[PDB]
Length: 463
Image (cartoon, rainbow, N blue to C red; front, side):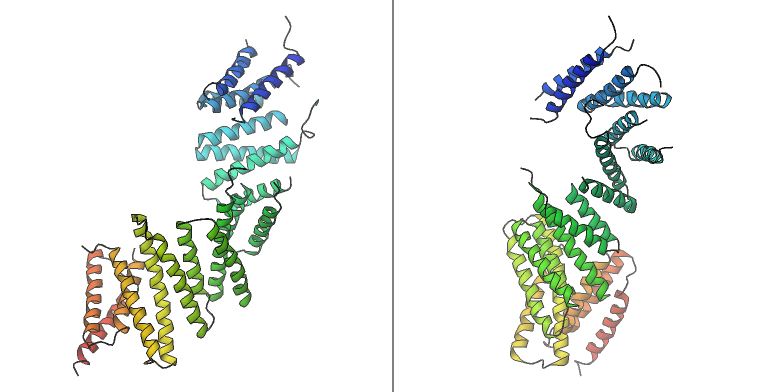
């Protein structure tokens, strides 16, 4: 009886790799266990009871890899981690192939472990050994022993980017997954381009964002081609990040018309695909960003009126979609859309006071439009307080100031209703401030303004 020759280890390699490869397809309670039983039969066939004879070293390294895949098959990886760290110690005492296989095993076990600090420390040590390899002091190859190193480099870099994005670490993780995108398109990419564009939204450089993002669009066009599509939601979030980039560029510009034209084309194609791909919550977000871009995209005086009735038609298309279901989720999104229509009525009232400042106020159709708008906004604020119990510092104070101005300037009734309405607004925020015991931001000067208003409307209508 001699030792294990090359033919026996090659037929064992072929059999084990072929059955594990046809088992990882996942076309069951025993077939995966039959692959694990064959591999533990090889484990018993090992029999452990320059350097030494390299056949034993190669077979122990590949059987440590097979023990690791058996442990990830059985989800009891403690003995697998023990055997692999002993393999790491014996390869330290005992190079390309062994260290890259040990590093892939370490990466997959510390990705299984989900402990952040140990996984990131082991990934930094494998990266340090990678930089040491870049320092640099057979029969049937895949591609010159280079394609295997290429794919495990991309896999290890994507997994360390995942461990880094489990932390905050945004700049270095973003650079690392951009390197994975470059290394992949030189030889999941939609979500990786999505988080690149989201980080660049969090950043300030948008030209490189548009460069890599249009590269993502043209490789979506030239992907080349089953059941799990996900492209609808993926480019839906891409259109979402497109309008968020439009939001931040309009915000930095406001605090020419080519932005209007690109907004027209991109949000038109976006709204077309958003009508294609569902939805309920996505459509709430759609009319949210549509109304918000209609607020931020200001042109002129007479251009404001058509834009206001445009986003009024937008919220009038929002409204009858969520009437039939009505969960408490509808109550929460009803509170958000009442805040949105409150902002829309604030913009409409700025339009109306500009019109009353520059043009004639007591005209018939203008009075009809403003009293219809006042009645609809009173109903909308009635629903907004119906979100509160009829029988956190910023939006409550903003809603109080908005309903205080609504109590103030919209009526020309018998001259006591506006006075009692501003009085109850003052007492409402007095109850708010003795209920919260906290200091406000602008409500103190709007309270002293409403107190002086209480004095002058206590004096002047009586005269």
